Length: 544
DNA sequence: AAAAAGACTTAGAAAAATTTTT
DNA sequence: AAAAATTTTTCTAAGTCTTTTT
Image (cartoon, rainbow, N blue to C red; front, top):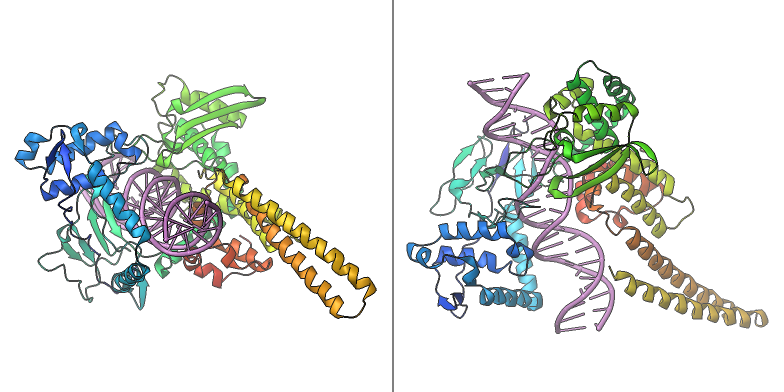
C-alpha cells in the first residue's frame, strides 16, 4: 500500500495545433501545396528536425513517411507518394526564425512566460498524497511528435499520436476530488488503486507500453524508496564475501544452469554488467546484457596483451552505448565460458538455461530483495567512499577538494560505463592571471620594499592590501588551473547520472561536512532537493 | 515456472536557463 | 547585443523488477 489519500488535478494536455502562416509554403515537386491540418502538423514535426541527422536516416524516413500518409486525406494520398519530393525548407526556416525570435525577444516577453510557466506549475505540478502536498515529476502530457529511438532503432520516426483525455487513466483515492476532463471530453477510466505510486497513465502507441505521471524525486514516496535503495546495498555489502565465495563454488557445480548463473553474477559483480533482460524482438535496437550475451559478444584469449584468461567483451548496452573490454578472468570462469560457448552459433545466447528471473530468484534467496541491480549501487557507492577517502588531500583548498570529489566521481561513472577546444580559452585566461598575479607580486615587492625604510603604518597597511591582492589572484588562478585539469580528465566521462542514481548522497554529504565543503558547490538545486533526506540526516562520520 | 502485463528506475538527449565571450 | 559555451532542468526512451495468472 502506497497511500490512503491521493488527489491531483490531472495532466497538462499538449496545446492545440496552430496552423502555419499563410506565407509559409510547402511543396511536392516544386508545387506549392496546401496541407490539411492533421497532415500539416505531422509535416511540421519533420520540418523541425530537418537539421538533425535523424532526417537523413532510412528507417527514420521510411517510418515517418508511412505514418504521415496515414494522416493524409485520399486526395493528398494520391499526390504525396514520396518523401524525397517534399520540401520543408520554408517550414523549417520559419520555425528556425521563430526560435531566434524567442532567443532574442523582449525581456518583457521572458518574465511574462516564466510567470505563465510558474502558475501552471502551481496549478498542475502538485498533488496531495496522504497528508501532504507533494510535487509531480512529469505533469505535462507528451506532445505528439516523432519517435526518437536510441541506436539503430527499427521504429524510430514513427509518429507519436496526440494523447487524449480518453487515453488517460486517472488514479486517485475514492475520497478525492476527481479532476474534471477538459470541456467536451472524458477520461478513459478513473481508478483508485493505492497499491501503485502513479497518478496518471496511458498506453503509448509505438511500443504499446504504459506511460505514467509520477512524483518528483523530492517526494516522500520517492526519496523513501531511495533511502531503501542504498540500505540494501549496504546490506549486500555485509553479505558480499559470502555471496562471492558462494557463486565461486557454484562454478564447480554439477549443473550448467548453475555454473551459468554464478558466472553471470561474476560479471555483474566484477564488471557491473546489467541483468540483461530478454528484449522483445523488433521493438527496439538490438542491445544485450549479462544474461543476454550472445556468444558473438565475447571472445576468449588464453593469453592476451600479456595477461592470461582474458574475456573480451564487445556488445552494445542500454541506449546502444558500446561495451568493449578485455578482462583477465578467474581460471574456472574462463574454463566455464568455453563450455558455455561450445557447439553454439555466434547468435546463440551464452547463458542459455539461465535467466534474469532465475538469477534474481537466487539472489533474493541469499539476501532479501537482493537484485542484480543492487550490485551496481554497492560497487559504485563503496567506490566513491574509498576513492574520496583516497584522493581528498587533507590540506587542500575547497576548489581542489572539489576536483578531488570529481576525480572520485569518475572512477564511479567509469565502472558504471557512463559515456573540446575549450582549453584554448582557459589556458589563455590562465596566462592572464599568471601574469596579472606576477605583476601584482611586483607591487608587493616594492610595497614590502617601501616598508623596510618606513616602518610607519600607512606603509605597513599598503603591504597588507598588496598582499590581499596577491592572494585573491592566486585564488582566481588556482581555480582556473583546476577547471582546466578538470575538463581534460573529464572528456568522455558522464557523471550526472552516477551522481543521480548510483551514489549514496550520504557519502557526499558526509564528505562536504568533514571537509567543510558546502553542498552547494557539489549539487544542483535539483540534486539537493532530491537528496534533502540524506542532507538533513547525514553525520560527518557517515560510513557506507 | 512461465510469461505477459504492469510499475518503477535509470540515462542520454534535448531544452532552457545562465554565464561568458565577442 | 548577440552568440557561444556551461550548466541546471526537463523529457522520455530503455531497462530492471514485481506482480498477476493461467
